[PDB]
Image: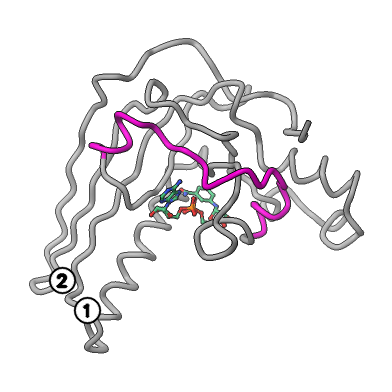
Amino acid sequence: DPPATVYRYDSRPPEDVFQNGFTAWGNNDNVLEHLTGRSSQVGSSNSAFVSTSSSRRYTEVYLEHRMQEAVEAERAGRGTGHFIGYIYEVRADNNFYGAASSYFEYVDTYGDNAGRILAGALATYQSEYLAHRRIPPENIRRVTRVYHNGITGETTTTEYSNARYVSQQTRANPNPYTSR
Ligand SMILES: NC(=O)c1cccc(N[C@H]2O[C@H](COP(=O)(O)OP(=O)(O)OC[C@H]3O[C@@H](n4cnc5c(N)ncnc54)[C@H](O)[C@@H]3O)[C@@H](O)[C@H]2O)c1
């Protein structure tokens, strides 16, 4: 079945996320622009989607990469090396859509052939799920905080549960996302 639980790395703390949920950047509803990295923060910063992963490890690799960038910066004399990152554990519902199936629906209908046909399961956004527009706070179950001390190298991990989380039987949508 589609996953009931997904994960999201984010820099923002639970005082924000546990109360307000996640809100997408904007109204850019183009799935292909989102999945290929064009409409999030380092691009046009207007995507209508919020990425998550069914694989906790995927989000841990993301956190580890961002922490390592802070470390490299300290060594280059460009920062103190400190880093705080968060991994949120989230209940998926019918407003969460598989990236792989959504990608294929889009490119089969509107794409050219680039990456349409030669696109295996491990290669094609294997574990990514897109929440459309919002991840409400009631879906956000808990968070792991990882703090790296840039000066001593000590890394400390803590956990917090969201009092606003609602436990209900939901899973991600079985169908691809389609706009409109
Ligand atoms: N985030 C994940 O764990 C994740 C899980 C599975 C797959 C992916 N694959 C994505 O990686 C790339 C980066 O994804 P995100 O980190 O989700 O990109 P965002 O732009 O949503 O978030 C980056 C940062 O931008 C900030 N932010 C994000 N949304 C808002 C907002 N609405 N308002 C203010 N700040 C915001 C916040 O600092 C956040 O950590 C995307 O191009 C896409 O390919 C990401």
Q: Amino acid at mark 1?
A: Gly
Circle on res. 93: none
**Residue 98 image offset from top left, x and y in percent:** 66, 36
Magenta-drawn segment: 14-36
**9 relative position to 86: left or right:** right
Circle on res. 79: 1
Q: Amino acid at mark 2?
A: Gly
Looking at the image, tell me whether mark 1 or mark 2 is earlier in sequence order.
Answer: 1
Dividing the picture into quadrants, the one containing residue 171 is top right
Work out whether 75 lies above or below 158. below
Residue pictured at 22% horizontal, 88% vertical: 77
Residue pictured at 66% horizontal, 47% vertical: 28
**Which of 24/125 is in front?**
24
Q: CA distance from mark 1 to mark 2?
A: 9 Å
Circle on res. 150: 2
Proximity of marks 1 and 2: CB atoms separated by less than 8 Å: yes
Dividing the picture into quadrants, the one containing residue 39 is bottom right
Q: Is residue 20 magenta?
A: yes
Dividing the picture into quadrants, the one containing residue 164 is top left
Number of marks present in the image shown: 2
**Closer to viewer: mark 1 or mark 2:** 1
Instruction: Find out if the beta carbon at label 1 lies less than 8 Å from the nearest ligand 1 atom.
Output: no
